Image: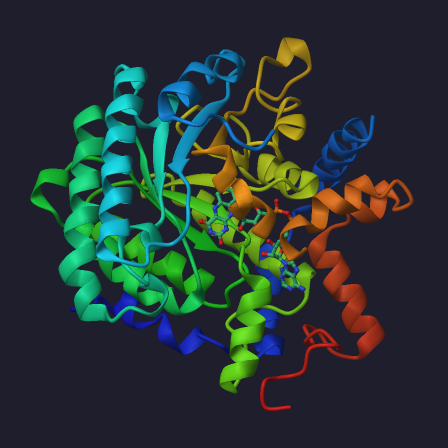
Amino acid sequence: PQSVSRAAITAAYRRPETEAVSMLLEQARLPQPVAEQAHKLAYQLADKLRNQFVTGETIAEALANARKLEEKGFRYSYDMLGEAALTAADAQAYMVSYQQAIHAIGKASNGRGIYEGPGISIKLSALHPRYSRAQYDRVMEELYPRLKSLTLLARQYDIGINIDAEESDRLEISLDLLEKLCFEPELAGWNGIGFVIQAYQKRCPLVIDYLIDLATRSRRRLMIRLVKGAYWDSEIKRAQMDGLEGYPVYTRKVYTDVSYLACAKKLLAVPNLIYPQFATHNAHTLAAIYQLAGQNYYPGQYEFQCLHGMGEPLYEQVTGKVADGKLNRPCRIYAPVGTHETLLAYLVRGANTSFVNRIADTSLPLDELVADPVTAVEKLAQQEGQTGLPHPKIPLPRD
Ligand SMILES: *N1c2cc(C)c(C)cc2N(C[C@H](O)[C@H](O)[C@H](O)COP(=O)(O)OP(=O)(O)OC[C@H]2O[C@@H](n3cnc4c(N)ncnc43)[C@H](O)[C@@H]2O)c2[nH]c(=O)[nH]c(=O)c21
């Protein structure tokens, strides 16, 4: 059974890009004081940037190697990576591996809790055979009890447990799993449940409204990892192959940047209901959130996140003491754990390296690198005669 907010999500599924962008544009606005500040900071972070991906083969080794950056203010979220589960036995192997990881992480956490201590990150596609194409009934029957069991194990140790986000046609299933989990009696009062949402989806703002509703109804604070989205190519491909009325995601990168900012504001507005975790390696996005979060930061207000191997050089400037030239804002490192061989997944994941490749391009000016998304959309509208038009090289599926 659904709440009104929950039922509201469907409509936005693949709504016209011009409409979606129009609704959101001004919501992504940086106040003038904020915008100038964010630009200056963004500039100095990217400029400083213009001047290894596996944390450990086992969780014990990952934990051993974590002190170095934890001492500097970083936090960690560990994920036992590997291929999607194909059989129930694969799923169970992953289950066993997650359980063992939680005992180890919990022990190392040693009562640090869900904010300051490390946490676990899980992938639903690891926990159910052929999840990408699995049926609702079977997921609820077989996946849910695993998710609940892992979550209770994390509560026992008081560590955060985060649910990943995958392809857009998995969204609704994942939300049902989240809703049921939030009403478990044994989880009452505990706020360590975490969930990923993807800004590149047109449904994202509506998903946020539902999450706010859910946190309210279930009397908790949700830990929400806001990312841009990792599956853009395949989202575009699948909609074309299926001949849909439109895309579930934006087709221009700047639109996703606009969406991320508008969504970040919505998250920050409700400190009682949400602990926002801003996962980005983009220097402007970081700087903007930093200013948007306002004055009088406190540790439990929010955190940044990044991928191991991609984010440290940026966040070395952010996490740490102000006396040392840092910003004193925590960053949680997402740390893949497993045999280095199984790192092939990393290589498997252009779209997702937009900013990091652009900052590597020393022929690209820093000022265009850290340009305001909203301002850029207005410029595009000026040139093209209308706001929020789809990428010119990507027509609708039925074209
Ligand atoms: N897991 C997860 C967990 C953590 C801790 C992090 C930090 C990230 C992920 N995650 C990956 C994430 O979704 C992004 O792919 C990644 O963080 C890179 O984004 P960012 O650092 O913000 O750099 P950017 O500014 O260059 O953005 C790139 C981003 O823009 C979108 N894009 C690209 N091209 C586009 C076009 N033409 N039109 C619209 N949008 C376009 C893409 O989203 C691209 O990624 C991750 N991702 C998940 O989906 N789910 C997860 O659980 C995690």
Towards the viewer: 22 or 357: 357
Towards the viewer: 208 or 306: 306
Towards the viewer: 195 or 106: 106
- In the figure, 278 relative to 330: above or below? below
Residue at figure coordinates x 78%, y 35% from the top left: 43
Q: Quadrant of the N terminus?
A: bottom left
Q: Tell me which corner region of the image, top left, top right, bottom left or bottom right, holds residue 155.
A: top left
- In the figure, 362 relative to 399: above or below? above
Residue found farthest to the left:
185
Residue at figure coordinates x 37%, y 59% from the top left: 209
Q: How many marks?
A: 0
Task: Tell whether 269 sits left or right of 366.
Answer: left
- In the figure, 3 relative to 189: above or below? below
Task: Tell whether 1 sits left or right of 399.
Answer: left
Residue 131 x %, y %: 32, 62
Residue at figure coordinates x 58%, y 42% from the top left: 280
Task: Tell whether 278 sits left or right of 371.
Answer: left
Residue at figure coordinates x 27%, y 58% from the top left: 87
Residue 50 x %, y %: 82, 31
Residue 237 x %, y %: 57, 74
